[PDB]
Length: 10
Length: 92
Length: 478
Picture (spheres, rainbow over the protein chains, first blue to last red):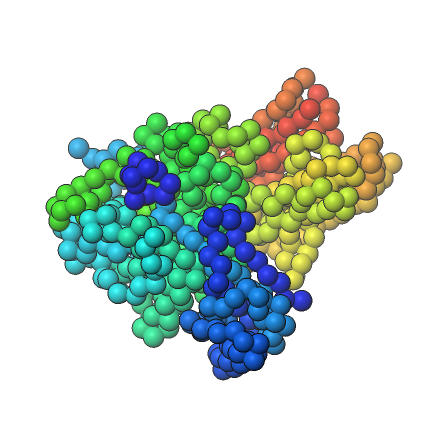
């Protein structure tokens, strides 16, 4: 779950 | 009969830029004339506007940077179907 | 060694995408990465808002790799073209996305190629203009695949997810469960067409030209379906959007999602399907799908309408309300084509109309109606594919039978080569269920006329919900 993927922290 | 729409998710709204959508069979030449007309009517009211893009090929219309003050005026232009305030999209 | 997601979409029997082109609207991409080098063309179209390097192209690079990557891609062959509509923070605008979609259509008109698939790995709130542009591009013959959204919310509240004619994709994990992460997770509900692997998905990392990273999201899920669609359209280039959607549903793994993950009211609305590639086994077959309307809302005279695609036939029509405050449903013509209309009751919160839309060429279908008798009956005097009933009152053999105070409607088709049978099941019960036999396609689902909430087809199973109930399934095959 990376920060470049909205809305994950990142 | 022309209506206004903006994003229900308030933080995602981008006020000050509007997509002006014209009726389905409106021709590119007509879209361009409608854009110039808005800019002229706005300027007479003391407002600067900028036509960022004229749409044709899927929807007819144009993208305009202007104060929302002009929306009542813009909704009365010929050929207008509806106007939507620009808003954010995000990588999913 | 095979990534779990690529195994998951592999069918139980098996043996791409080059005639097809896939457009990607996303962040910038590292096009020289070895997964995708020479396979992605960067258009250098760019329309992005100002901010407010490895990171700039991570999202797009990963998704290009899911679609077409030589080691970890779904459609390892496929040609891609990329447009930049998301900035370094992964943010774009509705206007920018519209200009991008318009650019694709213009490109096509200037230099026509084969089938086009457009992946939209992005979402904002519901947008009338974005949905209309998507619809217009779909009607122009382009296939659109979009992310359901990552908010653990109803996808109908988001665009392009909510956009008519676009294939909307939710995300499931290695246990085939919907992805959740707190208040975040896959969207769901009736605007989602199917789910696909979208957690822990290995693909190209823009950290380095040979690096890989696992990422999660409904875009990764949508990328699997974009890849599967490109493969399907290479094999059968003449597929219409409705034919492609029916194949994606038909070849999906069914009933593998635990519906407990979804909010209670969304369970009935959310398709329980996980995408898969078609088997080596494929000879004409009857394909049907269930189409839920938007909720009618609570107005006394409210109606919900469920429609089929232009090349589909409406073979049956049912309805459902959670309260059971319902005046049933009827099939009505509209622009020379039958639609499914459901009626709210006085004081009801609203109802759904639920169409069964099928690919049946050469079918000549009609409706036979009988208004209330003193019980009420009507027959195809042709094969019966569906029974419906509506009433205007507040409370109480190729043949349909209704309540004595209700109108009853039979969908009757002339479809030579079509065999249909009727299977019934009843018990003392919150839900009663009856399934067609393998190789048969459910065309109609209804309850024999103690207080029923509604009836709906789930795949080839007819479900009746009540508050001596008898489910009736009409099943057909070639």
